[PDB]
Image (cartoon, rainbow, N blue to C red; front, top):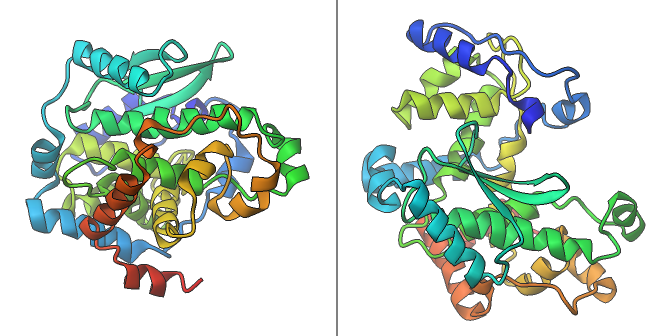
Length: 332
């Protein structure tokens, strides 16, 4: 991640803003560029672009603006104290108190990042924009999904690259990030998948636009210059001369996973899927006979499986991802 953050981001941001958004950032990066990863994520998909737009327009039709959506459904901005308090309550509820170091960061291009610093798990939380009703969801995403799946994975024969090849695993993504995104919005009253949708949309446009064009295009959905800056940089991570079209397509994984998981939710065993580790929903049957399940942990929010399934239905309705639409999307 650190590798894809431009090392001159601040200087370029000031140039952009002081130009009244007409300048195209010329980003630079810590040598060497991770070629393989850039290449892997150099193309945008349009497969779910209509679902993304559907999500965004559903928010805007109910709330008028992102700004109002955020305040009305997000609640108040939290102090550091309030963050630490909510996090501590979460770790206890999740039976993982004392396992993860928690750090508060200003450098983050997202709300949160789970890492391995000093060979040890670390949750970095962005202090800017952490919100009362939303923070719990970030914890369900980062700790209840990424962290638990990671620990469960470490117990499996596919715990490393060779194990994945030997047992014939499909990639973890987009199942990983799909599951995490659903989990973020799981117990919200208005579980719109705004971030997943806008990420997907931004990348799709970035593939054909300059930074300047993209920043302007987003005005239609979000006014705040600072927010738009963040979405633009994310969609163009790795791009040096942003006057040209190009994207880093990774963040399309969120909506991609959401749609596939919701589409197939009736045949997916969610506790097993989490227990098997970093695995695709498609490999569950394949891997079930070989999984080591004795000491695997399932998130607290999956104990009541009927309620969990009801929440998935609520998420579907809220986001206009109805059964018949999913079925036409993926005739699987």
